[PDB]
Structures are given as C-alpha cells and as structure tokens.
Amino acid sequence: KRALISLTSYHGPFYKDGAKTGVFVVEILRSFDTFEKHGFEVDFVSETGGFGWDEHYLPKSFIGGEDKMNFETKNSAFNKALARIKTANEVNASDYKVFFASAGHGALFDYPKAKNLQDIASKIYANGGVIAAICHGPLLFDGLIDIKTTRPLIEGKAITGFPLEGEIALGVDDILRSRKLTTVERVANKNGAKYLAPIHPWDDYSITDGKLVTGVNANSSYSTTIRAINALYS
Amino acid sequence: PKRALISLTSYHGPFYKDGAKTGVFVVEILRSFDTFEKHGFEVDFVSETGGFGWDEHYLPKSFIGGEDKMNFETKNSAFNKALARIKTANEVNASDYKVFFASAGHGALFDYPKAKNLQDIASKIYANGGVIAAICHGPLLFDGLIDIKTTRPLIEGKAITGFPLEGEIALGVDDILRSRKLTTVERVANKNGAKYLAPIHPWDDYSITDGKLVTGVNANSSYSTTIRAINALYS
Image (cartoon, rainbow over all chains, first blue to last red; front, side, top):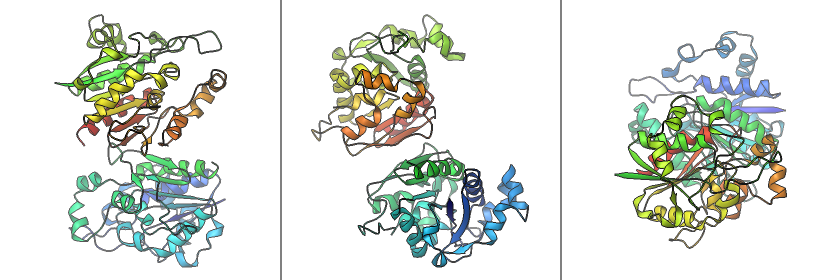
C-alpha cells in the first residue's frame, strides 16, 4: 500500500512585497501523517524533483502539534521521505494506489503544465486507483487526460478546491490577473467539471466523486486523505 | 419583507420495530427557523396535510438544550407562534416566499416523494429566482419535482447531499427500508438524474450549494445549510 504526494516545484516570485511562493508545508505534514497512520507507505514527488516553502508561510511560523516535531526531528519518517523526494519522470506509477496533489500558491505555475505528474496520476486512476487534490492542487487537472477516452479526466465530475473569494480575501486576486494565473473554478469549467464552493475559504470542506477526491485547503488535508483512503476501497 | 418557508413531514405513523412512531426531528426546524430569523427572514411552517408529529425516538425533551429548549418551551416565542400557525400546502401562496426549506426525520420517507402540493410551492419559488434547500431525508421531496422551465426533474444535472444509507445501517433501520419498500436520498438522486455526494460520516455537518439548490446531511448540518440557502439567494 503506497501513496504518492506531489508538491508544487515552483518557488519563485509571486507576492507584491518580493516574497516568494511555493509549498504550504502544513498540507503535506497532515497528509503524510494521516496516510501512514492508516497503513500506507508515502513517497514525495514533484515535476522537477525540487521545491521550496512559500515565504509568507514559513514552517516555524505555522507548524504546530506533533507534525511540528515531525518536521524538526531530522530522522523522522516525514524527513526521510522528503529527502528522498522523487522526480516525476523517474517514477513508476504502478507502485502507487493513491495520488495526492498538495499545493500552495506555487501550484499556479507548474501544475497545469506538469505533464509527468499528470502521466503518473492518470495511470494510477486508469488502474482503479485514487486521485486526490487539495487547495490549488486541482490545477493539476488542467490537461489531465483519461488514457482511454483522451478527454479530461475530471469531465462530468464534481470537485472542490481553493475558491476565488479566498484569493480576494488574501489580496492576491490582482496578482492572478497580473501574472495570468487561473483558479480551480476556471479549471473545473474548462474541463467539463462542476465546482462546488465551501461557505468560507478556511473551512474543512471535502468532496468524494467516485475515485476523484478534492479539498479546499490545509484545514481540509486530513479529511481529504481519509476520503482518498475510503474511496480506494469503494 | 423577506420570507422563508420550512416544510415538515406529514407522516407520524409506524416505522420502528419496537412499535415507536416516526415523524419530525424537532432540532431540524428549531435550528433552521432561528438562523433564518436572526438573518432577518420572517418564517412560516407547512406540511402536505397541515399536520405533523415528533418522532418518538427523538422526542424534543430528550434532544434539546440552551435557547433551543427555551424557544421550544416558551409559549409565545416566535418559533411556537409559527408552529401553531402551520399551513396546509395546497393553501399556500408560493410567490410570498424566496426560500423553501425541507426539514425531515424518517417520516419524510413516507410522504415527501408524493407531496405534490409541497412540490408545487418549491418549483414555483425556484422558478421565481428563489432557493430550494433540504436536509437529511428532506431531498426525498425532489423525487418527481419538476422544473417548470425544463419540464424535467428540477435536480437533473445537479449535485446534492442528504442522509446516507450508511446512516440507516448504523441506526439499524435499513431492513425497515427494505420491508416497507422505502428509498434513500442517493437512490432519488440517481433516479432523477442528479449526482449524490456523500459525507465522510452520517453525523457530519455537511452541505452542498449548487446554484440555487442547497442540501445538507442532517440536524448537525441545518445551520450551515440555512446559511448556504441565504447566501445562494443573493448569488
């Protein structure tokens, strides 16, 4: 039983104050821990094999509980996997039964064009596995193809993910226009899917539609991981 | 100024193996009424017959507390005044209301799929640009609910949630659904061309907004569903 968590590989500029974006560490900590407590062996991966933390969301500023210890303990299960982070094109998809797409505002840049991660995810899904994605993670769905039909994998599906209202609240909706970046909702409509919104951008909100599982944010990471595990055995 | 209509199940007869009668789950109407009122909506109640009864496994005294208890037990509270004024469905003018809210309880299994007057009110409210909301077994009212613009079932092409079969199994009433040939929300969704999206647990606060069609799983979802219903009205 193996799960594969993808990270955004982009960690360049984004924010107006010069600070760089990247991975939101809370997302992968919660997901990694939940998988491994439920009998899965987890590996990390990105399109390039590299990544960085969003600079407005530095680990020590946001991490709490026992995943704070997991991050800081150098020899932990989380750190052994993170140091072993794989490069997408080198990954054998048949090793994994669950694909989990973690995010951060970096996913706005690489995920829609991450052809190798998409290849991995679409193959896992083809063999009867689960594709899961949280926050900006569903951006990986843009260009994600059903091997059999050649149509978008998420066509006719219901998904959730980070809402436009969340970006406005964060004051980054202008950056989306400036840097020609998209939203999960746009990706949904572009690919024949329906987008379902949470009441608030910070809510723990999740959707299971067959073996395609989505969540709104890091606060939804645990629930989306549980949904992914349940979906695999459905 | 702005008015909401909360429907109750009409049925309060036999259901459980221990001889207990089913009916309304009071927490559903108490919580939705309050949330509507606190947001400036005047609220009226309705059922298909004009009558109702509390589910005997969920008697109010055994399940209410705080200002829910207060609102229920205070003789001239806004909740009690509206409940004593419960309307009969065929007498209701649909154009008065901007939101239809179907509360439930296992009683909904018996009358809701065939409550043609309630179905008429809801469709008209929907046609006039209003919102349809439903929690728990409430979405059973959607069975054969016609969109006047399409001629087809209103929930066709829509995403909904509601009380899962998993919930009936945990409650040990799933065998009663087979004996008495009663349905589930999931089965109503698939029969009317809708997609059913399940909660992780049958007791979760879980709700969906799809345009102006709003659904929740249970009483723990009634607040969130009412909020979603209000929000959807101005969408």
